[PDB]
Length: 220
Length: 219
Image (cartoon, rainbow over all chains, first blue to last red; front, side, top):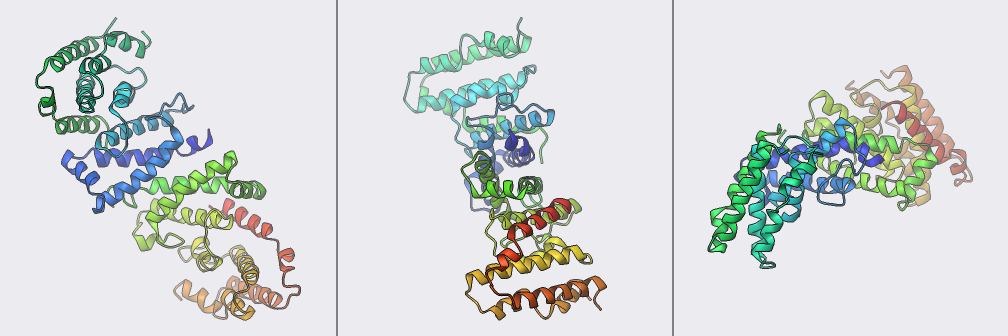
């Protein structure tokens, strides 16, 4: 498709700006998003408005799936990978409205795309994301904790790892499964449940994810 | 500049400019249909590009065109990007994709087509005369102003001073040729009946094709 082909430089430029704004120290990035009338806040708002428009050209869902839209060249795929990181970081800072269910479902495609090797720090980030999804889902008083936890920390994690790389399990993969199992149990047996956000504060997760996305992808 | 400011967005400005130059780079009837039928598949897609271009353009200018010296775009690639963006603003304007009056188009023509005090070329002066011609034809349709007021504005007497002032200055042989081609075109327009046959004497689609062809070969 022509417009998706021709707009790759814009997709890339806006994604890079978002990543380098929202990858700053958490206090600095949070300030930018929560003060739209500041100098940098106003500039971020215009960048985000253009980004929302360009993103809609590439996907009607939460993230961009390069294979699904025929984006096949090395530069096209590298750009959509950057875009997906910018989307994820903007979602977690609230600049985009993407629910925790979609963040969890797409986490490996965003941080370990193209059947790459899953790394230990990705696994740790995965576990903390699932923990925040659980804490947020509990706050809606919609479904019981058991149901939430079985979705977020599922029994088929090993088959999912094999499927995603066309495969038995690697050492990191089995460590993640074991770390996730332990976190599920701690979460289910914790009391009082309403205290979990003090135990796993959001600000700490924000700092975890920005540092990863910064210190694993080049900024500016 | 700072993150997310005018220097940060230069690749987006150039990319959207290049897209507008490519799409309105098509044959006149094709390009015109894209703009005039916003419901077609191409028309719908072009609309989304133009909405993005409108937003990025506002970041670079409050007016019709982008003056790099006015907003501090100092690096060579930055200055070349604003120059190209100006060509795309002008191409979009004559196709109806952007709403910029003939007055703004006339006033910014040399800055758009001959920036940086380059010596005017006879071809640039030709198209300048053709643009003034079309701006007159349109101004006489609207018929809010007397014929002399309109010919004054578009074919003015101080055309000599303007060419001199433009390059910090006596005219070049080419520049005095343009003024005489201009004055003669004015006399013909000041004395043409029916005044609404001028649309047939100089067809708009001919001008459009001349501008587009010029831009398509000089951007």
